[PDB]
């Protein structure tokens, strides 16, 4: 089997991408944030505290003839940005782009943090990291991809995120028309539960490539590119007037600037992020100070190849017995 679904930016900045997902019988379609940095499929629901729902579409398990309460199961998750959610668990039929999993754990939120309530466009998350990170207790549950894997034509999914435009998540096949050149594959460590890999270096604009190992995670659920402070400083030094602002929370730059590209290495291959992809717009409405799309990871503990980096590539998440990642230009 295969599946293919369009993923759409939630706003004009590409802050996140939503993909429609069918849950239950009859189907209830929710728009979920596919997140290769986590491993829970959780949704706003009829059980979510009413004051914490503000415009999201909810899953109502009582209206699904295939929903079953997973007795005794609870979940609770905290994300790298400080947001969180928790609740109980159903199993139900879940379909993405024509690919159907029966008995998928659907984690129903009883509580969500304010950032989720305040974003009416995201109805939940669909985790695509390794199932070892799943938070369901006392019996950990498998991700959608883990449940589908054995049925897929090939045990892979691909992320093709658009810049200011829709893109595609495919399951079970590699669309050879969706990229240019070849796909370069690189080793993955699953020891932390992430799609963790080592970039071979970087360049700023037309500058020389610096060969240096940068360990990080491929994370579709993170907006920006978070890299070591040395790398980030070298990038922003090429933008007149750019500076790190402690009050804003990162590097800002004059909105009148033209940003240089940023290149990262994948083996001997190179993925070029155009400068425009690094502009996240005014820090507040009407400001002439703009927020940068490349930021320091120093306060995270890991480097994160988020959407800024991934949307410059066609990315293969190869879930073979020994997982690997693939990157192609497009």
Image: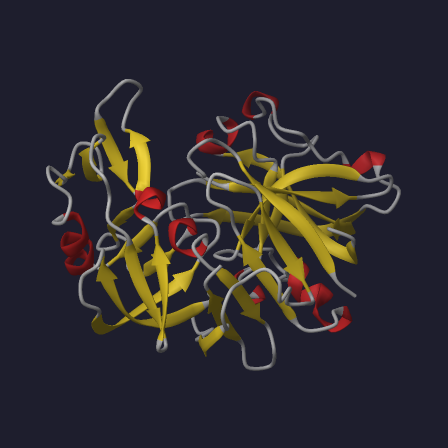
Q: Residue at x 69, y 73 (%)?
A: 154
Query: Which image quarter holds the N terminus?
Result: bottom right
Asked whether, in this view, residue 139 is left or right of residue 28, the answer is left
Q: Quadrant of residue 27?
A: top right
Q: Residue at x 48, y 53 (%)?
A: 220
Q: Position of residue 316 (x, y in %)?
A: 54, 67
Which residue is outermost to the bottom? 322
In front here: 320 or 2?
2
In front here: 242 or 114?
242
Q: Position of residue 165 (x, y in %)?
A: 52, 40
Q: Residue at x 35, y 54 (%)?
A: 273
Q: Position of residue 129 (x, y in %)?
A: 53, 62
In front here: 173 or 128?
173
In front here: 23 or 10?
10
Say if 10 sits above or below 275 in the image.
Answer: above
Q: Residue at x 64, y 38 (%)?
A: 31
Q: Quadrant of residue 155?
A: bottom right
Q: How is the image coloured?
A: secondary structure
């Amino acid at each position: 089997s295969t599946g293919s679904a369009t993923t759409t930016p939630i706003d004009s900045l590409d802050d996140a991408y939503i993909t429609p997902v069918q849950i239950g019988t009859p189907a209830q379609t929710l728009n979920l944030d596919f997140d290769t940095g986590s491993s829970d499929l959780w949704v706003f629901s009829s059980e979510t505290t009413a004051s914490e729902v503000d415009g999201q579409t909810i899953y109502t398990p009582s209206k699904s003839t295939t929903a079953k309460l997973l007795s005794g199961a609870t979940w609770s998750i905290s994300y790298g940005d400080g947001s969180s959610s928790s609740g109980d668990v159903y199993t139900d039929t879940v379909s993405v782009g024509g690919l159907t999993v029966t008995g998928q754990a659907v984690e129903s939120a009883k509580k969500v943090s304010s950032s989720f309530t305040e974003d009416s466009t995201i109805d939940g998350l669909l985790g695509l990291a390794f199932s070892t990170l799943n938070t369901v207790s006392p019996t950990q549950q498998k991700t959608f991809f883990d449940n589908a894997k054995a049925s897929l034509d090939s045990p892979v999914f691909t992320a093709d995120l658009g810049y200011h435009a829709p893109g595609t998540y495919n399951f079970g096949f590699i669309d050879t028309t969706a990229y240019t050149g070849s796909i370069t594959y690189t080793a993955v460590s699953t020891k932390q539960g992430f799609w963790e890999w080592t970039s071979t270096g970087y360049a700023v604009g037309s500058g020389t490539f610096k060969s240096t190992s940068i360990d990080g995670i491929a994370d579709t659920g993170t907006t920006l590119l978070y890299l070591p402070a040395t790398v980030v400083s070298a990038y922003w030094a090429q933008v007149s007037g750019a500076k790190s602002s402690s009050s804003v929370g990162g590097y800002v730059f004059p909105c009148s600037a033209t940003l240089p590209s940023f290149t990262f290495g994948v083996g001997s291959a190179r993925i070029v992020i155009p400068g425009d992809y690094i502009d996240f717009g005014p820090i507040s409405t009407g400001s002439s100070s703009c927020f940068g799309g490349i930021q320091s990871s120093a306060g995270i503990g890991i480097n994160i190849f988020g959407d800024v980096a991934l949307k410059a590539a066609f990315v293969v998440f190869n879930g073979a017995t020994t997982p690997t990642l693939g990157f192609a230009s497009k």
